[PDB]
Image: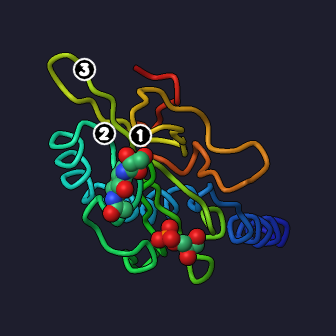
């Protein structure tokens, strides 16, 4: 070989040392959102029992049978709230992933003639405790967990039935 080959080798070493990386932030966000999903999954029993024994969905954490929203917290979750039978979880505003800072995800259920189906996805709202339909959360806010930061199973629309 000669000097040109060595220079090319050094250039290739620099090229390899200055390479790019894929988007691992999405995977870390999914891993951190799994905790919020697990925390929100634990309030299903109380809401279901109240609905079965009273005929209407709970309107607040008080008669649902759970603690204050500010007390249901984890490493990356800061609040879990129940409103008209809908469970919503909010992530922390610091020491967490940048993409899922102060964002919300929701869980809700619909009653069938022989079963009760549960859904998971972007935030939804219910207007009346005796209603059977849901809609989108808001149009004047940006506190929605992106599709890229959710598992493929936890991607449901408000019109799903
Ligand atoms: C428990 O949640 C119920 C939905 C609520 N009931 C009503 O709001 C009435 O049906 C009028 O809509 C109860 O008042 C709640 N009980 C409490 C807060 O102690
Ligand atoms: O009242 P909740 O338990 O839903 O928590 C409220 C929180 O402090 C910010 O909305």
Instruction: Pick whichever, 114 or 130, lies toward us.
Output: 130
The residue under the point 31% across, 39% down is 56
Residue 40 shows in this picture:
no
Out of 78 and 137, give the one closest to the viewer.
Answer: 137
- Residue tagged by mark 3? 112
Mark found first going from the N terminus, 1 or 2? 2
Nearer-N-terminus badge (2/3):
2
How far apart in space, not on screen, are marks 1 and 2 (Cα)?
Answer: 6 Å
Instruction: Classify mark 3: residues with Cα within 10 Å, few (<14), some (14-19) or many (20+).
Output: few
Asked if the residues shown at circle 1 and circle 3 are in contact, with their CB atoms under 8 angstroms apart, the answer is no
Q: Which residue is mark 2?
A: 56
Q: Residue at position x 47%, y 32% from top?
A: 156
Q: How many marks?
A: 3
Is the C-beta separation of discs 1 and 2 under 8 Å?
Answer: yes
Tag nearer the camera, 1 or 3: 1
Q: For the residue with label 2, is its CB less than 8 Å from the closest atom of ligand 1?
A: yes
**Which of the numbered marks, if any, corresponds to residue 129?**
1
- The residue lying toward the viewer, choosing from 44 and 102, is 44
Q: Is residue 72 above or below residue 99?
A: below
Write down the quadrant of residue 16 in the picture: bottom right
| Vertical relation: 64 (above or below) 96 | above
Vertical placement of 22 versus 69: above or below? above
Residue 5: image location, x then y, percent: 78, 65
Q: Residue 69's spot in the image, x, y percent? A: 43, 72
């Amino acid at each position: 070989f000669t000097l040109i080959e060595l220079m090319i080798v050094i250039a290739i070493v620099g090229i390899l040392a200055a390479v790019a990386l894929p988007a691992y932030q999405d995977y870390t966000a999914r891993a951190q959102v799994s905790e919020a999903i697990l925390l929100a999954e634990g309030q299903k029993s109380a809401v279901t029992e109240y609905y079965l024994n009273h005929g209407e969905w709970p309107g607040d954490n008080s008669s649902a049978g759970v603690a204050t929203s500010a007390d249901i917290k984890g490493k990356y979750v800061q609040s879990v709230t129940v409103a008209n039978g809908v469970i919503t979880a909010q992530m922390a505003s610091s020491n967490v992933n940048n993409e899922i800072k102060s964002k919300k995800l929701s869980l809700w259920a619909k009653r069938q003639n022989g079963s009760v189906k549960w859904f998971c996805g972007q935030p939804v709202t219910r207007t009346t405790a005796t209603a059977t339909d849901v809609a989108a959360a808001n149009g004047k806010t940006d506190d929605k967990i992106n599709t890229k930061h959710l598992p493929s199973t936890c991607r449901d629309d408000s019109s799903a039935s």
